[PDB]
Amino acid sequence: TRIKKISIEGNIAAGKSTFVNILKQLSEDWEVVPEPVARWSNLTMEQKNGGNVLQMMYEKPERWSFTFQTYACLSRIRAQLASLNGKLKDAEKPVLFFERSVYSDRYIFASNLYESESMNETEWTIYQDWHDWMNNQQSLELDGIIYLQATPETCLHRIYLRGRNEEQGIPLEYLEKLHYKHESWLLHRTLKTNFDYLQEVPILTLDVNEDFKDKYESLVEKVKEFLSTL
Amino acid sequence: TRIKKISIEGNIAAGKSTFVNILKQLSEDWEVVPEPVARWSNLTMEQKNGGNVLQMMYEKPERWSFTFQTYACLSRIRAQLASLNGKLKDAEKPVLFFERSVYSDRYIFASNLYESESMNETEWTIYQDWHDWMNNQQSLELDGIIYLQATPETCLHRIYLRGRNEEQGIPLEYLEKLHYKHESWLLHRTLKTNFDYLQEVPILTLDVNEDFKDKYESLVEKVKEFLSTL
Ligand SMILES: CCCN(c1nc(-c2nc(N)cc(N)n2)cs1)c1cc(-c2ccc(S(=O)(=O)N3CCN(C)CC3)cc2C(F)(F)F)ccc1C
Ligand SMILES: CCCN(c1nc(-c2nc(N)cc(N)n2)cs1)c1cc(-c2ccc(S(=O)(=O)N3CCN(C)CC3)cc2C(F)(F)F)ccc1C
Ligand SMILES: O=c1ccn([C@@H]2O[C@H](COP(=O)(O)OP(=O)(O)O)[C@@H](O)[C@H]2O)c(=O)[nH]1
Ligand SMILES: O=c1ccn([C@@H]2O[C@H](COP(=O)(O)OP(=O)(O)O)[C@@H](O)[C@H]2O)c(=O)[nH]1
Ligand code: NA
Ligand code: NA
Image (cartoon, rainbow over all chains, first blue to last red; front, side, top):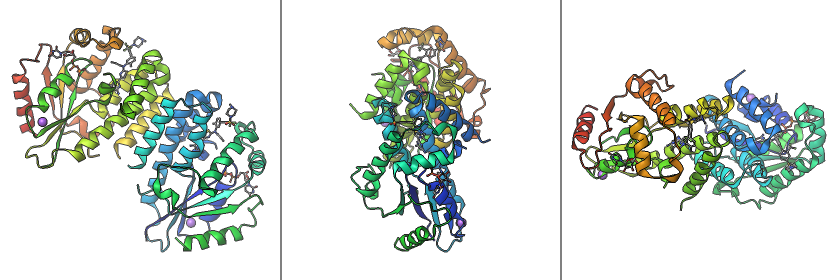
């Protein structure tokens, strides 16, 4: 029993947290690593740091993007490594579902902040150097990715449903930019990364435009079929 | 042959680079890891990043202290790990001399930037969390420390001798602040760190107020005697 590592990827309010909370309940061999940033957006020193840096980011992204992206990624690596070393000992078919990955940290979020001039060149090059190196110090490489594909308009509506005050100002245009990056990475596979194995990792794309909270059985059936091929 | 790891510590322009370049020549079992920041202060992507972030630091320390301290420390860990895995295979008595340590990064430099309000609380807490964790991902723990002890006035004179344009404005008061931290850490051993073994690590203190470039044999004799006790 080597733990299978599966990333759940998708735009803001696509339904990843909803989907991962469904999956965790369906099997004692299935565990989840919620995204650190998602927990900061609700006591611990990480949550106090994370809440401060997220609020400062909303005020002045061009000051705080580097600090935020480095702490978000380190927080994720720590939480993923903890689960990998903690859980599913004596699972028959152990699967750990990551809410997003170190790859979404860099290729979706940090990349967009650089493209939006919220990181300068030095900040972005330091970040990529840090990421290239931080990742080689290995056991987190993915067996597969599940892409929850929703339209920007769907994600905008779901930001409205979730009702976090800080997010109600997010424009469609931001969601469209993140959507294009996800489509380039996980559908067209046009995106060049510095992680050669990712070109070859299996991807399951699930259309989650339709509400699935009370009607997810088809989605899970595709997950179980995907898992059996890995 | 397990490599002995020895940090050379001391104030700005105490003579660490001079001393470490003397030591490296005296034995094929002796290798040195120059300090990354020292190389930025003279082609590689690290040097271009480092030169940019050092120049920006001089302009606006309260913007760049967090970015600088995180890149300086990661650059040091990478260079120390490279030497540890690269060199002194088939040395009889292998010794690797580190120009400063991850401990001087945090307890001398980053601590002073926090105390000078060039990092806010969140920046300083994120930095310490990053450092606590980054260090546990181990083989860099020190067998000993060599403290090159000079007066602030001596170090001020040696900044004048070395003649880097960017450093000629450094005030005595800065040197006195760094001196007090080194005395608390390595002489009085009053400084509380989060690394329990450091309380117990042997320290050799060498007085380097007197010029040693052509008269270092006494200093080296004390280093060889120190090494034989480890
Ligand atoms: C819920 C989103 C929170 N949010 C972010 N989160 C992450 C993040 N990083 C992870 N590694 C993991 C992870 N889970 N999350 C990164 S940044 C965030 C985003 C913006 C922001 C940015 C760029 C546009 S833009 O490209 O549309 N554009 C630019 C040109 N102009 C100004 C116009 C606007 C927009 C916006 C916006 F709208 F959200 F504010 C501002 C702050 C914040 C905290
Ligand atoms: C050669 C020193 C370069 N320098 C630095 N290097 C490092 C460093 N970090 C490593 N992890 C490793 C390593 N090798 N080096 C950290 S910061 C640096 C220092 C200052 C700076 C800071 C504080 C005072 S102060 O406390 O005296 N004080 C404060 C209140 N007021 C304003 C008055 C002044 C002074 C100064 C000064 F003088 F050097 F500028 C400004 C920028 C810079 C790059
Ligand atoms: O099929 C769904 C999926 C999500 N949501 C709602 O959409 C919002 C965003 O979902 P989630 O938090 O899971 O998005 P994530 O940001 O985690 O992808 C929440 O208010 C969910 O309750 C929904 O009503 N039906
Ligand atoms: O015994 C000594 C030690 C140092 N120096 C000079 O002092 C300056 C600072 O020395 P170093 O660069 O070694 O200091 P570090 O910052 O590496 O401690 C340089 O110009 C050295 O040539 C000197 O003249 N005599
Ligand atoms: Na479960
Ligand atoms: Na040598």
